[PDB]
DNA sequence: GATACTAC
DNA sequence: GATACTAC
């Protein structure tokens, strides 16, 4: 004859929780009219394959009700002493789900029954839990026993796109192959002693300039007769069968990249890297991406003093990377290998540098490597011939279960 | 874009057809593949008069069973079930009295007071070999010997206060009837530490008491019994194959490079066959590339060794090498295979020095067993975040490897990559799952370190127990 | 017509469970493997033992 | 949390009525919780042939 | 009952009557686990 | 598909089976020979075939010749290599005469 | 003795002859009524 | 799974060097027909190849 | 005369 | 302190 809205709200909450369970699979099952405590039992599926692991779930819902100490993170809640004991002597773990219709919000928390009485006061958070597709491995982690002789859980959750270390390079229209003006080593000394601008856009292999630039001015045509200019399509040598042309084009690209730094990215020799340079003694900041997520300060150069006194300098750290200039099936690529460098008085190559490099390589997990490759991509993509691309993205099939592992990698 | 695949962790066959992916749990759950007909494996100990009782105390200590120090990661640190009743080997290890020998302190000082580095190691290995040979021709013959070393010795043979001690002793012990095993003092006594040659103001570190015992007892059982503990599970109806692994090494007198090979196949019953050859293959210069005639002879020897057991020629031949397949060494193999009418062939180069990598947004690296087709080549991750140990064991980032097939191999790179991935957890020296190199490459590399000191006109055995 | 005898068998098994009283519960359409989950009531005051 | 025999006998009666409907080649199905004193619905079925008579 | 405690599994269940009746008789057990010669 | 097959043992050699019989003419007095071949599949199967040709006549004795006995063996050995990619290690021949 | 119960024509256990000769006799039973130049099939389902 | 035939690279290499046109087509169709016939006489007969 | 919603 | 389901 008359039915209040509270049971309606509860039934809606139970139905939406069941649908949220079903939209990830997991074969959620209902309950009879004789329920007491546990509101449902959920299996675990993996792409349609059952695994016979079950979790007990209790469902709570509200409409327009504000939770106790409602804020960004606090979200406290009070349980019942008489019901808890029902969840104490149980085989399956029991979880609690909270649902709100006003913001369409789902949350979950597992009740702890390790060795002592229950805390009775849940202090759940919104950054964690939140009952989305994430944190599905940490929910499924409560099926295996603590002993765990075998009996692992497959990585639930399907697909996540990753990237690769490689960079496409779009070549310019022409090069500037020239006539025979060969010099083994004096070709760098003539520009070294000259008073003109210094450039390293060339290599002497068989008597040719090998330049990307016009050999007309800027101290470039003092070694070769200016009448000899050649440029047709760059379809004869960069896409050519034999390997001598390939590994001389690699050196041409390396020299072209070496000239186009202008930040005094000094070239070492024992590791083939460009190891930065601070103009002034403090930390030298770098590119900020500003992709509407964070300011992303770089703090590249670091200064470290002695263990007890701040006067004398212990060491100064800089970032660097090594190129490779690889290729398959046209479209020459660049490979970036990030590396650290150590100086003593700013301009000093140091001589006990290996233990510091090994100790820092002991730290700096893969997230630092991904951030460094993103930084090095975004730093130099801001005259010509630097037509860099984006790191190619590949869609993997299995997501790494990072949710079930807490912290301290 | 690029086409990517993720393979599952392959299974191993141990015990009564029981299958699993962890050697520890498989051995503890179903026993070894080939069981011992007898009941007792006898062990002899050679060394100082202090390390022998240490070995005995270790044996009666680990007989009852030790516990692992894992609470957060229990799959990574499982307990040792013992050596009786609940044993994972279904056998008992006994040290028979009269099979032990001790080295006097009178002659352990003359070793320590020799200015030259060569004759000290020579007299040490000569004394140990003489004691073992005297033990051989009698009624106290053991199944496997232990050469547990003291600390005062381990300041001349190792710290040198300069040839190798293991590669010479394992070469001088080739004519005996039993294999040998070398153990340092820290493994058997957990109260002493040994410095590490240079920067001696420190001490070397080892694993816990439960991680040592699994590897030590598995190696001892395989060396003493002679029956293999596990093997890779064969699939459904597939063509019969014979795997060959080829690697190189350097002689320890100069800069000459030599080559080594290893053979393996399946049996008519239930058992793996892994062995080497009773010959060396000369030098022919300094290059890390083999000639044509020796490759043809190797292929002929593998075919003959298969036909002696199976009475028929195989269907396919799989060859793995740590070098590029040159156009001269890829013709002798073809000729030797076409002299016998073998149809399916495969030739793969495994490269370990490659730069390209896959990066993720999290704090953990990619899964173990990731494959990306880089336009006719394969990038395989044989180490990574294994979702069975519960973490990624190690620091920094894993190292992938590249598979490059020859142009006369009739198989796609994905099938070859899966076959290479299935051949990793065959190492009987260790019971760990995070293994990077295939078994033929490891077996080809392990033979060379013992072949380095064999010499000219000596006995070379094809038994793998003399090398593992 | 085998679906009707499967349904009859499942209903009779549930009735046999409910006669002594153990709070048996069925499953949905796409069930594969386990057909039901049962509790132990122990003459009132049910305990979570499935 | 001591349950009574009343819910037991109610569930037993509902299950037995469902079984008797099932053994006659009918189709009976129970309702939810928001039902208005109205239990499930039955459908007349021939030999493996529904007729949509409820 | 399916044996969920051994190693390799065992098929061929041998179901004998009387002792394995699903009735009130066996409930606590159900809830317990919670030459001769010839001539030519 | 085949319902059942004989269980192989453990450790045997690969083998192929041939069977030879004889039969009279339709109405006259001559004698031809007949043959059937049999072996084991690579997976879980069995192969049981006859041939694709008639073996002609040679008289009224229930006995083959030196030319009709070779061709059956060649066909049997050629059928095995098309499936297992290698020759068998054993040949088993059964006959009544 | 092992090759006796591989007769797919019958489900009996008291077979006397081995399978290959039985198959040869069954083939030769019907191979005698095929005319000259006609087709012969190697499938065993057309003889059993 | 069992109704799949793979021609070896040696056979395709053998029919890549026969300078008679009709002959090479004859060996190709003979090889494919032999594989199909071996498939037909077995217990893995498909419905369409 | 006991069990399930929710708001107080 | 609000509205529903079994029967005694
Ligand atoms: Mg609820
Ligand atoms: Mg070893
Ligand atoms: Mg018939």
Image (cartoon, coloured by chain):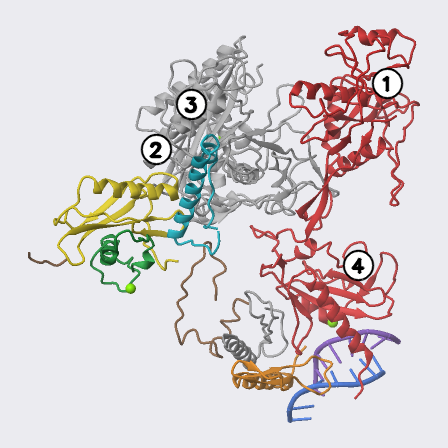
Chain colours: A red, D orange, E brown, F yellow, G green, H cyan, I purple, J blue
Choose between B436 and B458: the one closer to the eye: B436
Marks 4, 1: nearer the viewer:
1
- Please name which of the two marks, 4 or 3, marks the residue nearer to the observer: 3
Give the percent coordinates (x, y) of residue B255.
Answer: 55, 12
Q: CA distance from mark 3 to mark 2?
A: 16 Å
Examine the rendered structure and indicate whether residue D40 appears above or below residue B66. below
Q: Residue furthest left?
A: E40
Q: Is residue B260 left or right of residue J8?
A: left
**Label 4 lies in what chain?**
A
Q: Which mark is residue B296?
A: 3
Real-space Cα separation, disc 2 to disc 1, in angstroms? 69 Å
- The residue beneath circle 1 is A214
Q: Quadrant of residue B459?
A: top left
Secondary structure of the residue carrying numbered label 4: loop
Residue B142 in view here: no
Whether labels 3 and 2 share one chain:
yes
* Residue nearer the viewer, F3 or B384: F3
Q: Which mark is residue A124?
A: 4
Please report, as a chain letter, where disc 2 is located: B
Q: Tell me where residue B101 appears, x and y as whole percent.
A: 41, 24
């Amino acid at each position: 004859k008359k039915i209040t809205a509270n049971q309606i709200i509860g039934e809606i909450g139970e139905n939406e929780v069941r649908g949220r369970f079903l939209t990830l699979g997991w074969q959620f099952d209902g309950r009879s009219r004789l329920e007491a405590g546990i509101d449902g039992i959920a299996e675990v599926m993996n792409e349609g394959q059952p695994m016979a692991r079950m979790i007990a779930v209790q469902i709570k819902s509200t409409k327009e009700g504000k939770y106790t100490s409602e804020s960004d993170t606090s979200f406290t809640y009070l349980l019942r002493t008489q019901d808890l004991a029902y969840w104490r002597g149980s085989n399956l773990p029991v979880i609690v789900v909270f649902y709100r219709q006003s913001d369409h919000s789902f949350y979950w928390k597992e009740v702890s029954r390790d060795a002592g009485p229950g805390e009775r006061r849940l202090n759940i958070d919104k950054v964690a839990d939140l009952f989305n597709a994430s944190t599905v491995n940490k929910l499924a982690a409560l099926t295996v026993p603590k002993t765990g002789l075998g009996y692992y859980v497959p990585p639930l959750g399907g697909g996540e796109d990753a990237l690769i270390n490689m960079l496409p390079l779009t070549l310019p229209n022409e090069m500037y192959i020239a006539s025979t003006t060969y010099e083994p080593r004096k070709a760098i000394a003539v520009i070294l002693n000259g008073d003109g601008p210094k450039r390293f856009d060339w290599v002497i292999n068989g008597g040719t300039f090998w330049s990307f630039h016009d050999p007309r001015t800027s101290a470039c045509s003092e070694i070769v007769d200016i009448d000899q200019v050649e440029a047709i399509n760059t379809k004869e040598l960069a896409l050519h069968d034999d390997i001598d042309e390939q590994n001389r084009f690699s050196h041409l690209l390396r020299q072209t990249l070496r000239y186009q730094t202008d930040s005094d990215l000094g070239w070492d020799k024992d590791h083939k890297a460009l190891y930065f340079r601070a103009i002034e003694r403090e930390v030298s900041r770098n590119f900020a991406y500003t992709s509407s997520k964070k300011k992303t300060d770089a703090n590249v150069v670091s200064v470290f003093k002695n263990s007890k006194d701040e006067t004398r300098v212990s060491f100064v750290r800089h970032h660097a990377f090594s190129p490779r200039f690889e290729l398959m099936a046209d479209q020459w690529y660049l490979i970036i290998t990030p590396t650290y460098y150590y100086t003593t008085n700013g301009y000093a190559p140091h001589q006990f540098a290996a233990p510091l490099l090994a100790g820092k390589k002991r730290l700096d997990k893969s997230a630092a490597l991904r951030g460094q490759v993103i930084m090095w991509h975004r730093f130099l993509t801001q005259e010509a011939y630097l037509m860099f691309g984006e790191p190619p993205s590949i869609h993997l099939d299995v997501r790494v279960p990072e949710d079930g592992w807490v912290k301290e990698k | 874009t690029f086409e990517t695949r993720i393979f599952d962790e392959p299974e191993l066959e141990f015990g009564d057809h029981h299958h699993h992916q962890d050697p520890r749990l498989g051995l503890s759950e179903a026993g070894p593949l080939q069981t011992f007909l007898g009941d007792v494996i006898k062990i002899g100990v050679v060394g100082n008069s202090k390390t022998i009782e240490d070995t005995r105390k270790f044996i009666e200590t680990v007989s009852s069973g030790v516990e692992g120090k894992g609470e957060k990661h229990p799959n990574m640190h499982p307990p040792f079930p013992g050596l009786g009743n609940q044993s994972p080997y279904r056998c008992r290890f006994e040290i028979e009295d009269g099979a032990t020998a001790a080295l006097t302190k009178s002659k352990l000082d003359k070793i320590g007071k020799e200015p030259d580095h060569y004759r000290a190691v020579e007299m040490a290995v000569d004394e140990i070999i003489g004691e073992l040979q005297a033990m051989d021709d009698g009624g106290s013959r053991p199944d496997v010997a232990i050469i547990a070393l003291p600390v005062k010795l381990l300041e001349r043979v190792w710290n040198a206060k300069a040839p190798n001690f293991r590669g010479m002793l394992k070469a001088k012990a080739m004519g005996l009837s039993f294999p040998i095993q070398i153990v340092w003092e820290d493994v058997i006594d957990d109260k002493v530490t040994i410095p590490q040659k240079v920067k001696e103001s420190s001490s070397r570190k080892i694993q816990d008491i439960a991680g040592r015992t699994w590897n030590l007892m598995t190696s001892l059982y395989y060396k003493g019994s002679g029956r293999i503990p596990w093997r890779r599970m064969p699939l459904e109806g597939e063509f019969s194959a014979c795997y060959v692994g080829i690697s190189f090494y350097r002689e320890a007198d100069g800069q000459q490079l030599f080559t080594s090979a290893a053979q393996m196949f399946d049996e008519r019953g239930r058992g793996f066959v892994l062995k080497g050859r009773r010959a060396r293959t000369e030098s022919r210069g300094r290059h890390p590339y083999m000639a044509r005639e020796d490759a043809k002879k190797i292929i002929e020897d593998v075919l003959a060794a298969y036909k002696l057991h199976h009475k028929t020629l195989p269907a396919r031949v799989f060859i793995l090498k740590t070098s590029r397949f040159k156009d001269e060494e890829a013709d002798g193999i073809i000729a030797a295979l076409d002299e016998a009418g073998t149809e399916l062939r495969d030739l793969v180069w495994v490269q370990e020095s490659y730069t390209a990598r896959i990066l993720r947004d999290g704090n953990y690296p990619v899964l173990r067993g990731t494959f990306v087709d880089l336009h006719g080549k394969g990038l395989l991750y044989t180490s990574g975040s294994m979702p069975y140990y519960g973490t990624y064991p190690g620091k920094y980032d894993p190292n992938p490897l590249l598979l490059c097939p020859h142009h006369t191999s009739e198989s796609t790179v994905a099938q070859l990559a899966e076959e290479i991935f299935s051949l990793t957890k065959v190492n009987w020296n260790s019971t760990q799952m995070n293994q990077r190199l295939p078994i033929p490459i490891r077996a080809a590399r392990k033979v060379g370190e013992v072949l380095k000191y064999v010499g000219e006109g000596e006995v070379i055995s094809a038994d793998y127990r003399k090398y593992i």
